[PDB]
Length: 119
Ligand SMILES: CNc1ccccc1S(C)(=O)=O
Image (cartoon, rainbow, N blue to C red; front, side, top):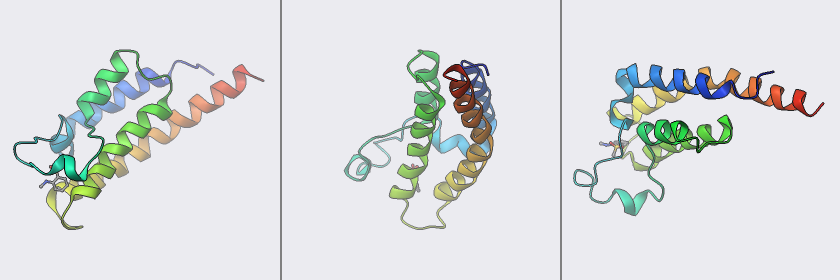
């Protein structure tokens, strides 16, 4: 019932994601010189360094907010891809499956801890 435990759990999951070769295209903001039309397609850029820095700054109040930003990395990739079999899109699908498999318990434990706090 530790209400604060999600933060270190999210730090550890971000570390695993940065160790994954599939996270390479998503570790830093998309290069606007290489993809000059990116901001025409994508309203809210997001990347894993921005997520990690937001967490370390103490600017997430809950793991749901961190989830929303990570899911935005994956939806931006889906929105930009010219095809459903593109290399970078396919890397984002595998990384998304890995992230969802691991964030499930972090979200459940946090929500359970908050319910216990208000019992
Ligand atoms: C070729 N680049 C690509 C393809 C599909 C999805 C995302 C990207 S991006 C601009 O985020 O690197």
